[PDB]
Length: 286
Image (cartoon, rainbow, N blue to C red; front, side, top):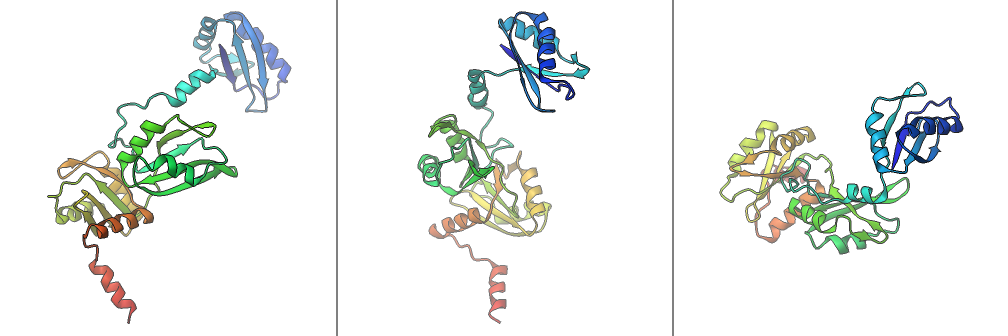
């Protein structure tokens, strides 16, 4: 039932603005209260209406409205339930593994101060193999975390099940986290008939491919470059597309992700030894 009025003149006193806002907005209907919350240019007014019909009239009619010489910006003041709906409504079904924002990284926002790595593993290990978890502090205290899984499906499942669920006193705000750019591309969804020849030749369009590491039991591959920029181009240009001849999932792979990938191939008996790498080891021993 309130509106929020921004871009008020800094030379006016709080009282002047309070009285002015009241006088201006009472024209739309009965006004319940007017509050000024400073200061300077973050200074804004709240005008509360008895009837929501009046609030709507005032919002609709005050687009590009001049007030005390200023083109004020006036928006609905969001009540707690509407905001909860805003901040927690069911995710759009368009959001799946192939969405341009989808990554292997779960953003976990709204953490409480006391949040521990053990808590996060306890809730989020159910949705997939965790590669790493990084809790970050905002202004000094834990506020959010990046939790990286081995694939994208796991992030989607975690979001679906846990978004808006409480952890301690706080509702989790889950989403796709951006992944830090690296020089290594990760691909998922490759048929076992895809050849290394094809992958190397295809990804060479983005720059010289240092090597490809194809886990053919899992249908995943690393495509490694010597430049972060090439991997960035490969990721960006591959995101929408088919890599022969299936819609592919694609992300960056950081060091921890690569290590997990290699271990997994070793455990399954797939060779990860590389030509140029052995040559290097030969070089050192000389």
